Length: 129
Ligand SMILES: Cc1cn([C@H]2C[C@H](OP(=O)(O)O)[C@@H](COP(=O)(O)O)O2)c(=O)[nH]c1=O
Ligand SMILES: [Ca+2]
Image (tube, rainbow, N blue to C red):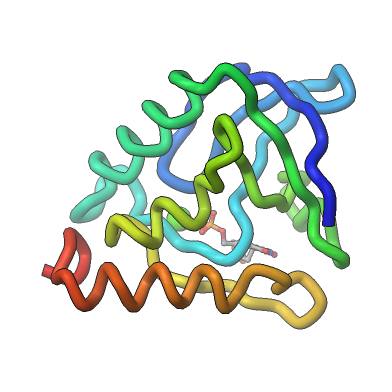
């Protein structure tokens, strides 16, 4: 896989963000994770965590997997990096998302995510508390 440039347009919630990619505004949905909706327990914390991570970054990058790049809603499907740190993995490591929506051929980083989730679960963090 490879990283491509993007710039933040607006944080949306724990697992979605508006980026400009190849000069076009797009909503991106993070691969392999499920954050609680804003109305749900840990939803506000998930949204705040992802907001702070993308707003604080000097450099946002997008990394598509090998399969589908857009979902049925037109959202891009990617791993998102803030100054080289993967947002998808960080949400797992903090107990603010569950590994979810793992479709064959778009799951390059599954085991990295599950590892992070196991560590969060060990620590009883957030969703696992
Ligand atoms: C993460 C992801 C979600 N989706 C679709 C499945 C779900 O469809 P339904 O809307 O029919 O449930 C929806 C969940 O996204 P959200 O968790 O953003 O709601 O997005 C994909 O198709 N591919 C993906 O890789
Ligand atoms: Ca969600």
